[PDB]
Structures are given as structure tokens and as C-alpha cells.
Image (cartoon, rainbow, N blue to C red; front, side, top):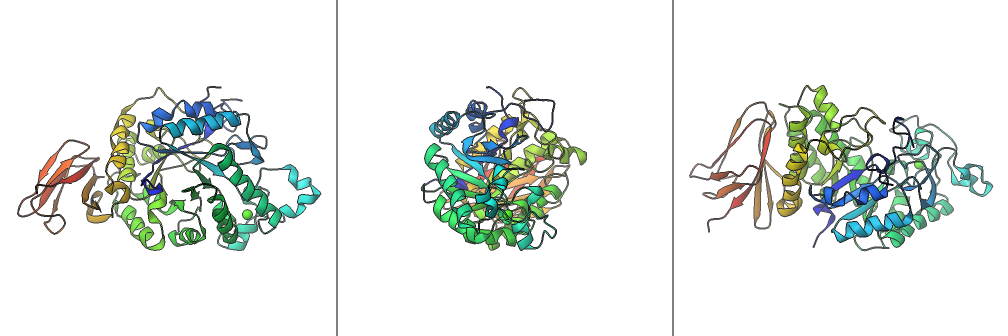
Length: 445
Ligand SMILES: [Ca+2]
């Protein structure tokens, strides 16, 4: 029985991915990417082990809304990205390939100068125009105009009804499988609770992925009490910047995050892990700034995501070491004829997560970490895997005891084909610099 903790998500900003059906030299303009472009790359995505895609919003936007987040019409596809038919086609085609489609949904606000502002029957549809002054004050966070965006009043039953109805409508119309929920910390928990109860009732197993941009796992985790299934893991991202983004950096922060997640969240396996997104600098730029090779960095970093708990979420272009700084330079036009070195690697590790249940459902034990060389063990049912990640500049040796693994078994490697024979003293792993290995325990009984 496939569940959401089994998935891996390829995350696409639509206008910036693939134009098959507008000024490319304007960093804040439309580049032309559309839904037909997404559909044409489903096999491409599936091959790297992704079982699901998340699209940025595709509703009709206010002028300039290339990214989709400035909604105008909640009941219409933006003509820049194509038609309702195109979208239905995308979902059908993904479904043929056993892939899920999550759409990006905004309940918090509409685009700048939205017409409802000047509609007398919808004056009560908005909070008084106010800046968010104290980003630790929940009332301001919830009533303020986020980056000046007209902020909707979900306490008004008309707004609450309009939004929920619209959300349900797209599920019925196109058979999507989830929503990534925008600006969740800006909308009251009592609304999300009802939204979740109602939207998710349209379709069995319909998944909500919340964006609560906080570095405090307890803050995010409380929203899990209000019907949102999973969350983008911003606390992990903080760890990623200090660990995976720099060679010879301890990987302990990453595990500490998990240890905290498992305790704070009811569903810690539905936390979306990411090396970057459309709101951060590119991981490639983090690596370059650290005077590291992006190629080996990304291969190493994505191996952690694909071997750790949660739901891996990879931003389009990561697989070609896409460079980029602050929004909008992190949204460059995708390249489908770049070097395939990371793609070929991902074609090993991505699918490997799908093929070994312990990587999707196992526990997550730290057997060893010292200065960037980490060894982890995951167990699920009869299966035991051991993941070793060498984040250092040299070959590393790690000895595991017969108290950390059953005695006298064998460990087969699934990245570099390798075998490790246990003895009376335990097991010895040796990894070259900046390499990882996934071992599955082999039984001799
Ligand atoms: Ca709000």
C-alpha cells in the first residue's frame, strides 16, 4: 500500500521549465514555459526516481505574475501556461506513469490591485492594508499584507467558502493528487482545519503539503495538528547549508534535525527535504561560494535526501548544477542538453529509494559521525540498510561492531558494487573522498 512517505517530488516553476507552445531576457518576465512542456518531460523526470511533481500555481494571474503566485481568477488556467485541457492531459499522462501531481494553492492572498479590492460586496473580503512589523507576532503574521499582497479574510464565511469551494473544484475537474499550500503561517489554523477536512474529502489519500517558513520545527509541527499532512522542511534546510553545502562539514546537524522532527511532528516522514527552492539561492551557488565542486556536492547532497527520512523534493535544474542567486536569478530557464553526469548518478540513487523500503519507511539510527563521515542504519521489517556518506576530503574508515549489526552477515553495496564480510569483531567500511554507499544486509541463514 503506497503512501505519501513513499514519494519523491520533482518541483517545477512552470514558466521557467520548458516552452513547447513573453521576454526571455527579462529576469522578471515570462520565459514561455508551459504545461505541454511539463508533460513532454514526464519520462525524463520518472527516470531519476521521482514519483510525483509539484507545479507552481497555474491559475490566471495579475499582470507580471510569471511565477503564478499573484492570483486573479481561481477558476481558470493562466493562458501563458496553456489550457484546462492541457492540464487534464498532464494529469492523465502522469497517472499513466504512476506519478502524482500536486498543484500550488494560495488561500492567503490574491495579486496586487486585484479587482475585488474595488468591489463593494468584497470590501469585507480583505484585512485592512497593513505591513507585517513583527514576524514573531502571529496576529500580525496572519492579518498583515505579505510583501504588500492583498490579504484575504478567512474569518469572513464568504471568503472561507469561496476558497474551499475553489480548492475542491480543481480536484473534481482535473483529478490532481495534492496541494502544496502557500503562506500557511499567514492563515489561521482554524481555517486550515476546515479546509483540510473538506478539500481532502473529495478524494481518498489527497495530500496537503504546507509551506511554513520557520526554522523552528515546533512552530511548523503544530500546524500538523490542523489537518495538513506534511510540510516543507525549512529547519532541515538550515542544516543543509551548514553540512551538505560544504565539504568537510559535519553531517551531525542533519541527523539532529531528524531526531527533533521525529519527536515534534506526528508525521515526521512527510517532511519535504530540499537543497534549495524558488525562494532561496541555488545549492550550486552555495557550493561554489564554499569553493567546492558543485557536481560532487550535489551528488553527495542528493544522496542524503534520497537515503534519509521525509519526502525528497528536488527543484528543477538541480540535476544539471543550475547556478543562480536571489529571486529571480534562481528561476533561470531549464537546459535539456547539459552534461548528464548528475542525471546518470540520480538514475541510480533516486530509483534505489523506490526499490528499498527501508529508505522510505525504515527507522534512522546514527551509528557513527565524525567530521563529515557519517554512517547510518535504517531498518524496516526484515530489511536493514546501512548508509555511509563521506563528506570529507579524504578516504575514510569506519568500524561497526557486532552490537550495531547482526554478527557474521554480509553487506552488499548498491551504488558502487562492493561487498563487506562481517567477522567476529564487526564490519569495516572504507569510502573514497566525497562518495556515499548504500548497503543492504545480506542474510546467510
Ligand atoms: Ca493572511
